[PDB]
Image (cartoon, grey):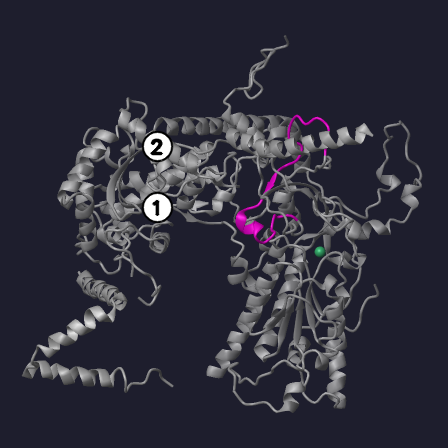
Amino acid sequence: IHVVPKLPNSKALLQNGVPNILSSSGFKTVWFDYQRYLCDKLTLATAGQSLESYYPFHILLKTAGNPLQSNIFNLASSIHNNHLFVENILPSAVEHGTNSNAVVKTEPSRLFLSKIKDSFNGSDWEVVKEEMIYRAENEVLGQGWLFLVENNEKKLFILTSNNNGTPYYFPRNQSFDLNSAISIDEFATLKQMKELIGKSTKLNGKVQDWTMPIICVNLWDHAYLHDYGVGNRSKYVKNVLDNLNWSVVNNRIFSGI
Amino acid sequence: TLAELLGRSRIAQVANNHKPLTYTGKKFHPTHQIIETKPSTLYRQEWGLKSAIPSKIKSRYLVYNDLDTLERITTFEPRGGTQWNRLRFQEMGVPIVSNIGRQNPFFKYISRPE
Amino acid sequence: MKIQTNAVNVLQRTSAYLKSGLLKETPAWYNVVASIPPSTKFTREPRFKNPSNGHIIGKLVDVTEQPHANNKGLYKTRPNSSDKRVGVKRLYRPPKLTYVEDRLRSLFYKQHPWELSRPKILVENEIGDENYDWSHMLQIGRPLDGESVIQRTMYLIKTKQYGDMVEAYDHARYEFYALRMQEETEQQVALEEAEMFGSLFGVSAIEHGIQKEQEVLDVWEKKVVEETELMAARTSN
Amino acid sequence: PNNNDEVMLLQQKLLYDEIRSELKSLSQVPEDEILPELKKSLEQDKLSDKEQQLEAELSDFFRNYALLNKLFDSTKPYPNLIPSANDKPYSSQELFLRQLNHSMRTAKLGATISKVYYPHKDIFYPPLPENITVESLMSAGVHLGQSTSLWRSSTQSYIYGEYKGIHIIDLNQTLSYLKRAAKVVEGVSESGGIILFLGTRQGQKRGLEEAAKKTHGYYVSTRWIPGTLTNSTEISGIWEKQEIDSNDNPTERALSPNETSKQVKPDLLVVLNPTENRNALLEAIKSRVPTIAIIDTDSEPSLVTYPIPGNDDSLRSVNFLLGVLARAGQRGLQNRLARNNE
Ligand SMILES: [Mg+2]
């Protein structure tokens, strides 16, 4: 059985929500309700099978290449992504419930701001945030996820997913919406991706992708509607990126010590 | 009691089957329940049967008749291939239709003495 | 094999060694075994009830208990030959455990042969943790399968909502069909929706089968050719 | 905040590589190109008061730490990683360490797993004998006996019934016998006795080794040499013995050859597969060594002091019962080491 993880300072979260982003009702929808909804569906889908003993991140990797397990993949991807989003927007990862700590001033580290300049042609963090808000509004028509990811070449770049798209495995990033029209450049990217997946010799037709997320923003209606409303998702993404917990985001960047 | 627990055990859930494990006639549908073991349990020859399955077996799927026999072996075949036939049918997305136009057996229809 | 005596009396044989002086020092196990005596009866024990179905073992129905005529229309006035044979052996033979659910399980998989193709894991997690409310078929912790139907049928007959087992079974079967149809659609739609957002898959199930069949059909091609050439030479004789 | 500290080192590390690379460049150049021109410069140069300072400061600095020194004497994790340049992509080793970082923090986000059986936990987290239930024994498969065709009718009193062509062992009796056996292991461990765990079926070694380790006991997983107990001087005399205190610490006292040839008999023998170890059981009887064994429906109960009715063919059932006995021994050992402290 997959159970909803306990969050630090949960009593505060159920009373005052997440300050500057979500209210108490908004956080109950995104985490206490939706995370319960996802975990229960995952348990029903995976109970009695070998996947029941694996964590959601491992389930999505195991099932990423199986077309008829997409339902399990979607549930595992959503569960992992939601706790990636709830973790970097959380007031404090440490449990100051008995310490009553009200001073958590987290700021981008030097390694993060050095990789931002290197990967974005000298752009500042503030400018990159504006590009992230723009990318979300023009690339994610409906539900999806906004990620700041790091690849095998030490370069930070921006990835957007439609519905439950994993950042780890490029064949399942779901960054192109094929319901609408696509340019020849987008079709080239899809055609090149298909060729890479066909070069793999494995009988499971799986490739190696070492991309890892650094920041996760939930773009689903379960996270913003109640507090911002239809059409105000760009005001929601702005608040999230301005109130990130950088103790978690800094720890996601590999240092090598 | 122990008897109540046993009746609901996972081994009890598998219906008794003595059909030949090696059948050379016409096969139209699955005849044996596929048993699956997780990778961790396979590493320890644990399948939830009475005895350890020989380490030579690398598949994670088998079908069996008897938990134990007078020959002191389990009667099993290390195959689970009827599941792939079902999943390949699902991938072809062709619904099964009645050539006689009978009522759908999976719906509780109000039938009459016609 | 003979009932052994020397394995359970190690304490008494050791005590003779110590009392005589043949063994100077008391062994470390000596005190422990003395405080926890071994069981040394090794007897065959009678049993008077089948724990599975509660059938009484060892009860003889006397002719006084059969006053009415039988199915043949005859009264029973004297013990029959079976009543006059000592039945001590039945007291000691391990009772055959039987369950009504076993009959339904065989029926379910005879009616739905392809449910057998859904892999089942026999490895238990923890039987003591199962907190199931069989008012509904779905349960957190276990898959939807034939056993879900059987347990639902038993709950219906146990709550007396239905009287005949067949009626309870049919009611449970339809609940099972509804849940199976909702899952077959969630999987089809999830695949369709993913492809519409740019999901790519290396090998499909149909493709996997074609590749495996090719590997076998290639070895078969070689052997056929070889055995169609030995025949030609051998037949030439 | 303190990244600069590491940056200061890397700077030196880069400089060191530059110095070494061009030290090797000058090792190829012929001496005729450099030496005569170099000497000529000195022939055309005049030393100054300062130049002379280093003429003798370096002579001593090189006559102290290079010539008149002792050539020998009479970052902690992964200290041999060769980091890649900040412009170059991650190396294969760095990607492995980058993945290990992810595995500790992120890889387990989203859900926790409850009520799922993990095989390794039977060995490393065995339950205490008082917390064992019929359900737990049944979950491990301990109730699954042999085929009714292979019945050894001397086990009749342990049988609960027959089901699916096999005899079902009565777990209510298994629990009582297991508790009794566990108390014996605890007693012998608390008394300082030698506990030997014998099991020769494939896969049992891991359970056997951990059981011996946590009880400070001994194990045999490969083969029981016939005569190990009755012919001990011809088989085990050559192997080394040691003296230990009440805390099980080696005293370090050298042992007289008289003390190193004496038979060292186990105080308690635990046998996982007694049907294949008749030799060991008969030697234990001959040597008055109490024994514990798992007794399946085709196994003779009277051959052991403390039988445990149970399935002996499944590694889960065996490792479950072995784990309980091993933890019972551990508690006895911990109670003996505690009474010594206080
Ligand atoms: Mg056995």
Residue shown at 75% from the left, 32% from the top: C230
For the residue marked with disc 1, what is the amino acid? Trp
Is residue A208 a member of the stretch shown in magenta?
no
Q: Nearer the viewer, residue B113 or C189?
A: C189
Residue shown at 89% from the left, 27% from the top: C73
**Residue D263, position in %: x, y?**
68, 83
Quadrant housing the N terminus of chain C: bottom right
- In the rendered image, which residue does mark 2 sit on? A192
Image check: C155 left or right of A225? right
Q: Nearer the viewer, residue A22 or C55?
A: A22
User: What is the quadrant of residue A216 in the picture?
Assistant: top left
Is residue B29 a member of the stretch shown in magenta?
yes
**Residue C223, position in %: x, y?**
68, 34
**Residue D36, position in %: x, y?**
18, 73
Which chain is disc 2 placed on?
A
- Given the current orientation, which residue lies at the most extreme top position? B114
Question: Which residues lie in the magenta part?
Answer: B23-49
Mark 2 residue element: helix
Which chain is disc 1 placed on?
A
